[PDB]
Image 1 (cartoon, rainbow over the protein chains, first blue to last red):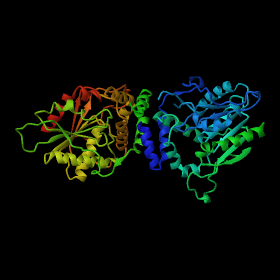
Image 2 (cartoon, helix red, strand yellow):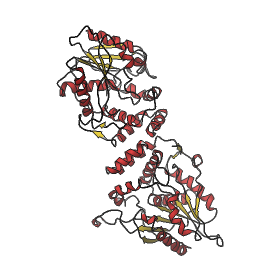
Image 3 (spheres, rainbow over the protein chains, first blue to last red):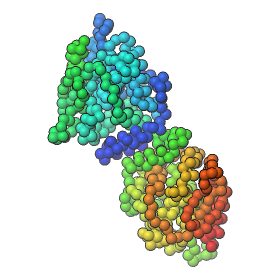
Length: 278
Length: 276
């Protein structure tokens, strides 16, 4: 119903997705923000979408889902996936500050990361943590991992990057900008208000900036095996990418479906990798 | 109660009026637009707000109010002013394209000016026309004047610019950006819609850019006597400006109140100028 949503839907139809994201990023600068993690206007209390075994709880790594940037998204993007972890691993999902307008936006990415970090650290206690993220959420998972390591002196035991397209390897995202945009108008996990579209724009901007910090935690790179649209392989690889991953796993489905009807395949790869890492 | 209005409200409070207008201009590019002055999605039929003497039926210049850019404006802009033209001059208020649920925004300024030109010519008949405008409306009045002259073979009899701040002379209005922002809200008779705020941002950008050309029509420059905000004496003149106007008149009030509280003084200056 909001004007930003109408403008955006029109932009996607006109193949100007990227161009409009810049507008959202520019517009978000006028939204009230929180400059310190304490000022965050929301309880980032991680939701335990899945509970692990009751017998062995000492030392086993817990999974923490890092909510992505989708304006129509939320922590439940991990619901389907978490199913496979019931009785296997504790699966927590942490909201992304500034979403679900009365929610203050983070002044910068680091502030949002510290807010999540504190919520995660208290929720995990002394159990090893393995961050997991999808698409934009994958980039955030890594950024958060490095933040925990460098700024909080608490590095996660590992990072699960599901279909990440980091700076320098985003030609596919550009070529498939339309299907990605249309993906934001399919359904919604939370009402996709103009406020949320602004949050997404701000985070898209944050994630485009230079972030030299590289986490020392091992990485499991999970990749979709079905292309989202036509690609012409002469351009190079359309698949997700990450430097020096510890393990790589190709799964059924495309960028979206890999986390839906094919989520069990992702969970399987993650469960095998966790056993290998521990 | 749209988000654009909420952001603008915050921008004004943060003294970032100028920056937000740019965002508005950028966002307007994604709104449906009309490219042909015939493809305009709305009826730009002028509204007669005042009737001139019934005795003098032989031409006599008619006043055309050129609706300004304020997102909180519209059909009520010249109500108060027109009351002073009753029994003196016919006064027609022409709407600004893009403000009347999802009216198409003009692809460029010329397209909007041509749509207005046709409506005005259709309504004024063969009577001489004198365009009148305030603030952004003043800049628009001149642009329309020139457009009528060069593209419709109908140069107006005169132009009445009320407190215009053309490019190169906008420092005052820039320094008083917050006051303009606050004025728009204080003037809301209803919450400014996001559609209109976007229209305002777009026209604002049209009017900041290169407008090669000057109307040959005589100009009456009406200036506010009181500054809208603080102004350092060492800084130059803060008053509205126009090059070589035919006549200059000063009325009481500031950029806003000159029209809101001293409309009669403005009307008086106009009538005296027309007689001449």
